[PDB]
Length: 303
Length: 305
Ligand SMILES: C=C[C@H](C[C@@H]1CCNC1=O)NC(=O)[C@H](CC(C)C)NC(=O)c1cc2c(OC)cccc2[nH]1
Ligand SMILES: C=C[C@H](C[C@@H]1CCNC1=O)NC(=O)[C@H](CC(C)C)NC(=O)c1cc2c(OC)cccc2[nH]1
Image (cartoon, rainbow over all chains, first blue to last red; front, side):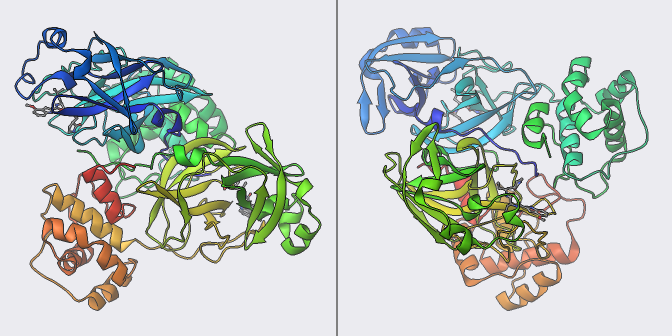
């Protein structure tokens, strides 16, 4: 029993992290086969940061302008290209620890594990959900760029996030491994705002089922609601609309607990309208929306 | 910026996880040099667990009754012994992935990363605080025993927890790597209850230091207190008393902010005696008690390993 926010084991990714230096700038890179992937803003100076013409800055660089260190070993850069906001440095050595991997673009509401790194060395691991406004609520300091987010299915690492920026609000923004930002953000040194954030309703519901599966039922009620009437109330409170696909994805949790999805929607509606009134759910005083139905099924099936 | 519960990178420990089977009972073990450590109840059948005599169960076992596997690769057992509630199995191969390590027994309030494992295969990693009642709020399913908890210092992995049991309340209990349970529990299939839990004062203070570092300091008052007086008051609110070691490990955060530990204690006392009103601290109306002083430094300074 028990429900906890947990990240995938990070070993397979730790073996890929390297340090990439250009000029006075050092950050992290991801070393897969004979290519190192890192944020392209590593090539920018203090002055270039405001409005960098990256193609113009990159053409002026040589392979020897990039220092790549894997532990104590320096990797010789034999080629450099740019795919959107990701710099790709070809090295003369293939990473022997390269796992089975793929590059994927994650959808809002889905979760992934972040391996926060500094100077090419792992520092910590934590789960983040891609928010509807395409930010993530992570923990990143100076030099964390190039840290990656991933999921692990079987032994295949699906990389979905590379870290680039912290917004003034303290949330974080980045790209996929094709270098395309999640959200309307740009890799320039400017204060940038995200769109109005919304709450991931299907995840809140999964988290309520988790609370029930772990013995917490105080928030349930004898009422039910139609999907549309629930969505009317949800949107009033800046919650994302619930789709029939979301309802279906919640089926397994509904079958395990015997609580129809629309019955749990009526509980959430009551919570949004009455609040929690000092009560807590799984130790939280707020409604948590960073747990997917899959994250709940993975931990609570059979309990 | 950002404050998150963050596990240690788990790679060094993943490379030490193996499967240990006795009969049909399989759980996890920890392979370090040429020894595998696992819970001793792996030698118990389902019926034996109700009331086991481990010394007697073990005398009937031989090296050849133990199946240790790294994946599907068998490691031959060439010696066995019981140390408290931990079985030690000597194997004929030294783990080439063995990291620098030590075995430590942690105090209540200290945190560690749990590498949840099933059949010797790592499933997930999460942070746990040892509660004052010597349970942890983990997430564990059948077959999870032998999963370990650890901290990383520089490059040394300090193992401090091995998982053994789930209490009726849904919390979890286990041992250090010398097989000594945390708390008054035993490895027997019996309904066991943990004492009343309490809030971890030193970690709440750390969380308050974290708030100050980030500019959230409305709760600072112009009072101080003695350690004894604060301890007596705190217990009335179900808070743990502070030890000298607690004061010591708050030293760095005290120096960084310039707020003496006993001054922060007086501020916390007022929050307990007056509440927080509708105000929040670091965005929360609840005081957090599962971040140690080091956890705060980790988050705000970016330590690597
Ligand atoms: C090492 C990788 C860091 C990650 C950051 C560091 C602290 N924590 C992290 O996550 N990335 C960067 O430093 C980026 C670099 C750009 C060229 C993409 N820039 C920003 O994140 C940033 C600039 C800025 C601003 O500039 C006027 C105003 C207000 C907020 C601002 N944020
Ligand atoms: C694989 C390792 C599991 C961890 C468990 C499995 C599910 N989640 C986990 O954490 N460990 C075990 O199965 C232990 C076995 C030893 C005590 C011999 N037994 C219990 O955990 C247990 C016995 C019991 C009880 O006995 C009458 C009453 C009420 C609650 C109870 N729990």
